[PDB]
Length: 266
Length: 276
Ligand SMILES: CCCS(=O)(=O)Nc1ccc(F)c(NC(=O)c2csc3c(N)ncnc23)c1F
Ligand SMILES: CCCS(=O)(=O)Nc1ccc(F)c(NC(=O)c2csc3c(N)ncnc23)c1F
Image (cartoon, each protein chain N blue to C red):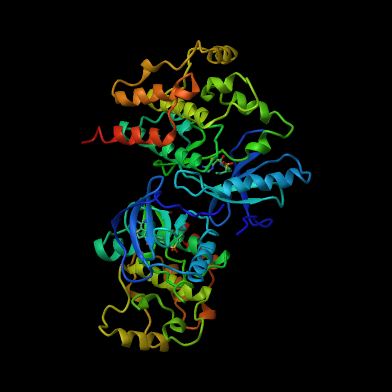
C-alpha cells in the first residue's frame, strides 16, 4: 500500500520547472523519474495532512493517457514522483519548435487527449488547467496529461487562453465543471488545427480577459487549415460554446473524434 | 480508490488467450484494454475473497516497465483489466516473426526487463513465471512485464492450468524449481535464472536446448545439473561482459546468482561501452 518513498531512495538531478506550485526536477528511482518538489519548506500538519489527501486523488488514476503517478516524498521535502517522459510537451512541439504534424497525427493527439479526460471525468476529477503545456508527447507518440492534481493544496494567471468564460470572469466560488475542462480542450483543438495560440492579434491581456468573459471575443474558427475535416470545426465550435451547458461531455466528444477519424485516410 | 469496474462497462472483443485458466481478450474500456477472464465457472465465496486479495498485489505496482493494471471485474465473470499494448511479446518477436534486433536495442530490451524486475522485487513480489511471452514490447520499444498476477489463486484451484503452465516454462525454470525438492523453491534468484534465460534468448535469437526434442529428458537433466544453456551460441558481436552476466545469472547453484540492483548496474555499464 502506502506510496511513501523513504529518503535516500530518490536521486535528484537536472532542473526544469518554475513559478510556485513547485519545482520539477528529472530524477532517478528505479530508472529515470520526474520529481515535482513543492519546496513549501517545513510543514506542519494539517498542511501535511492535506498533501496526503491530495495524493489520494492521484492514486485513483490508472490510464495510458494519464501521467503515471509512481509515489510521493515527505521527508527531504513534500514531493510527487511520476514517470519521466521522453520527447517534448505539445505546447513545445506546436509553438516552440513548430513541429508540423501530419493531419492524421493531429487528430490522434486530440483523440488520446479526449480519451484521457473522459477517464479523468469518469473518475470524478476536474483538471482545471488543461492546456497544451500539460499535455505531453511521450516518445512523441503517446499522450500523457499532467498537472491535474493539487487543486486544494493550492487553495490552502497566464493560462487565461484556455479559460472558459465562466472561469475567466472570476465570478462565483467554483467555475470549474467538466464543461470548464471541455472548453479548455476546445482551445487545444483549435491549437492543433491551426498550430497557433488564439487571439494573437490582441496585445492586451486584460482586454482579452474582459471580452472572453463577456462573450464578445472568441477564437477564430476560420484559421483551421484546409486539410482539416469540416466536422472538426463543428466540434470545436461545440466545445467552445460560451454557455457551458451547450458544451458536450467527453464520451460524446470522444465519439465525434473517432467517427470523423476513420473517414479521413479512406 | 477501489478498482472494481461495474458490470457491462467493458467491451470484450478479439479472443487472444488460449489458456485453460481463462481467456485474454482485446477489450474496450476508456480505450483499448486487455481483459483476462478467469472463467473458473462462478465462485464460491470465498475464492472471491482471495481473488480480491490478488488485486491487492496488482495495485502495489506503478512502473513504466510493469504492465499497467487498470482494474478488475467480478460482475459478469471474474476479470483483470490492463492497458492494451500495441506491438507483440518478446517471444513472438524472437521466435514467431523472427525480428532481428539491433545489438543496441537488444541490450536495451534487457535493461528494461531488468529495470522492471528490480522494481517488481523491490516491492517483494516474485514473478514466478518470467519468460519472453510475458515481456511485452509496447510500441516496439518499451518492455511491459506481465502475467505475474494471480499467484495464490492459480496455486490453489482445481484444473490443468496448474499443470500446463508448469510445462509451459520448463525452459526458464531454475534447477531449484525443476526438482520439486520442497514446498517453496521460488525466489528472487529463480527469477534471476529465468531472466538469465531471456538473456540467452536475446543474444542467441533462440530458445535453449533446441536440439533436444524429448522434453521429459530436459527436466531430468537440468534438475540433475547435467544440462545447461550452450553459451557458445551468443552472436559473435555480443559484448563479452553480457556473456559473463549471462553465466553469472544462470548459475546452477542459486546463491551464486546476483540480484537485480547489481544486474542493472552491469547492463547499464555495458550499454555505455558500445555506440561511443
Ligand atoms: C499523476 C500526475 C500528478 S500531477 O501533480 O497532477 N502532475 C505532475 C506531478 C509531478 C510531476 F513531476 C509532473 N511533471 C511535470 O511537471 C513534468 C515537466 S517535464 C516532465 C517530463 N518530461 N516527464 C514527466 N513529468 C514532467 C506532473 F505533471
Ligand atoms: C500486471 C497485470 C496483471 S497480471 O495478471 O500480471 N498480467 C496480465 C493480466 C491481465 C491481462 F489481460 C494480461 N495480458 C495478456 O495476457 C496479454 C496478451 S496480449 C496483451 C497485450 N497486447 N497487451 C496487454 N496484455 C496482453 C496480463 F499480462
